Image (tube, rainbow, N blue to C red; front, side, top):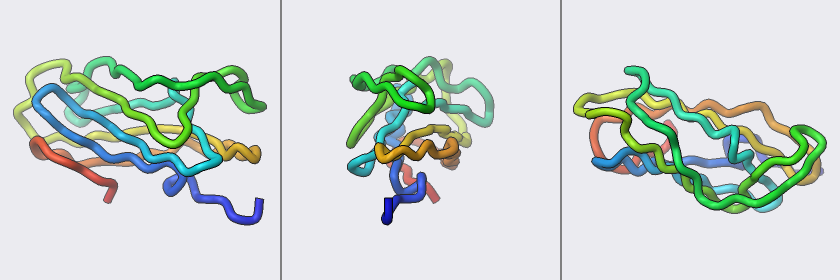
Length: 123
């Protein structure tokens, strides 16, 4: 393809932090998709987040990871808090996706410095 996005532009996260935990939204460029099963969150301090629930994805089979549940256009991931969170923390999101034309990008790691409820964007 003559005009492809770098992966951090193809798959763009934002956070909504609330009392119940962290809701992640992704905006995904047309002709790209994200692997649902490869979206991971890690925190510092560790283990503030519990098991995420995912918005509905769709079936895809490709030459990189075979059959996978994937996202086009958008995705939402809801991380509940695993325990009481009354302190600032760092959150690193890792996610991986492809261009439909046949490019499998390396995983992207995006860090957020969280200090209370509100909206956060990559910095």
